[PDB]
Image (cartoon, rainbow, N blue to C red; front, side, top):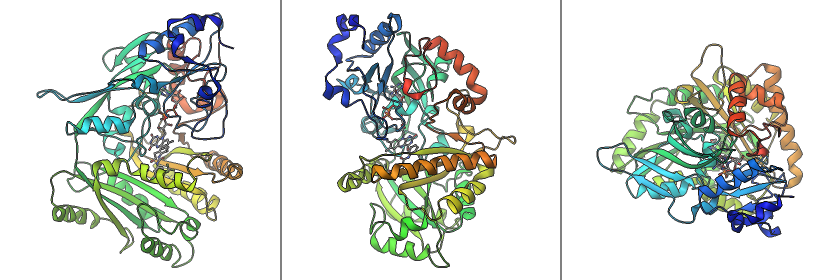
Length: 499
Ligand SMILES: *Cc1cc2c(cc1C)nc1c(=O)[nH]c(=O)nc-1n2C[C@H](O)[C@H](O)[C@H](O)COP(=O)(O)OP(=O)(O)OC[C@H]1O[C@@H](n2cnc3c(N)ncnc32)[C@H](O)[C@@H]1O
Ligand SMILES: O=C(Nc1cc(Cl)cc(OC(F)(F)F)c1)Nc1ccccc1CCO
């Protein structure tokens, strides 16, 4: 398949063509798409990626090039059949994380694009520092999350991970190594952020830092009414200047059957907790439970002072009386909380299963209409494995000049919701039902005039991508022709056909 001259290059020592090597880059976390590449490239340095890209770009027979972080995508975005998958991890040979915390200067962290957020955290904490915004799962690459947005519970305050980047090193689709920021090569900087790897491979990111907390007072608050749940979530993300508030705000939608027929205990809830919650979800018939998940960061504060601060906050809210659930953990334990969920799922053989996940950004004015059609009609009697997340964010913390898409509204509403359908197929036979629900959610939004944006979008037609990028589409097409003229990069995204 690949050109013969590729195996004569200085970088050919980093090309792995064996069946066991290519099999490791043939599937992703979704476990639904199988597309083996011709080879896996294990670069020692970012200049090796530049050399591979340049060779393909100047070749008589250009081949697709796809970087692979942790393969934590589910629609074949990191797959390169007929081409080369770049195992980004190989760049992590030696020291790839540098913390700059010199007195009388703004602190930052330079991290390789291949570096895991868990490893960035470990390095910065040694200096009493940490990035401000986190994904829920830390075993994701810097380059992988920055090519999307990187959303989580702190984004309402500081914006997504793409709003917390000073600069990037990018290997373009021509093989050119470019350093970019708001002040130098700003077109590539804005394009790469949420750019789905279309304009180049991120090899370095300079990440914004803030003083690190030591501990976290972590709460889950139960609601039986979607209107009260959303008013409280919006209140929690709308008083950012007040000293009485959460550093992290998320939420969860638990369908009636998921509680009643669910596990005996979870890493957060005991047996007695789940028993009371099952009782609450069935007091006047079957209802879904909506949880607000809040986290309050602290450093040297005493246990009794934290109790008083949390009480002052909870005293403002309208959750079901007697239903606050509380944990007190280290900052690392809070940020790495999903690692414990993964451990439990892997023991049960419920982790390495298909994940036909769907992530939507829903306008706040339509959130109750969305709830009615999706949770109260479509899924009222459903019992999917996995979870459903729901929480609001602030548009004023997102830079709309970056590629990443958020919902557009006629009244410029600052609030939008992230609704994440993280349902798993315990058996590969459960996939068609989950995909039918995914399509039913999207069809419902279409019929109702609810103009959503998919987060981690996946379309197989240019009509889908033009609708997704909207006003930015023409600018995106222009930047693509400039930075990846041969459309070599991350073709698994399926945005651009090969010219
Ligand atoms: C599996 C998963 C994903 C996930 C999550 C929890 C789990 C269990 N929680 C998330 C969260 O709380 N917030 C959020 O914003 N995203 C969350 N995700 C999704 C995840 O961020 C993305 O899927 C992202 O792509 C990171 O994954 P990863 O490092 O594993 O990258 P990949 O799957 O291999 O590649 C995805 C696409 O990006 C391109 N890519 C990869 N690395 C680069 C670099 N360095 N530069 C440019 N493009 C890059 C791939 O080619 C592919 O198209
Ligand atoms: O995967 C996410 N969170 C998450 C949180 C928990 Cl407690 C468990 C979990 O399930 C599983 F199976 F253990 F991994 C996942 N989030 C996510 C995913 C994709 C895009 C955006 C997001 C941010 C939405 O908050």
